[PDB]
Image (cartoon, rainbow, N blue to C red):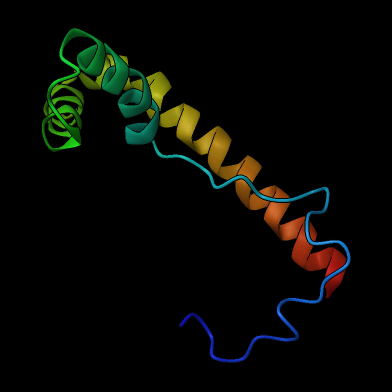
Length: 93
């Protein structure tokens, strides 16, 4: 029932287009994307209800000296995602 208004069962020519954001990621998403596999690999039986909590407790307790690069990476990816999106909205105006 998503949007009762359906323009002739979707009548678009070119839906997918270049220069498009890919959703940035936070320092937690990076350390969680990798750690989520380390735990899921050592224990695929447990779901994200424990895997994500494992990366959250490890990262949260992860010395700031090691997180330095992590958060910094999220900032570099935060500008890349916000940069591409800004260009799109600025190109369509």
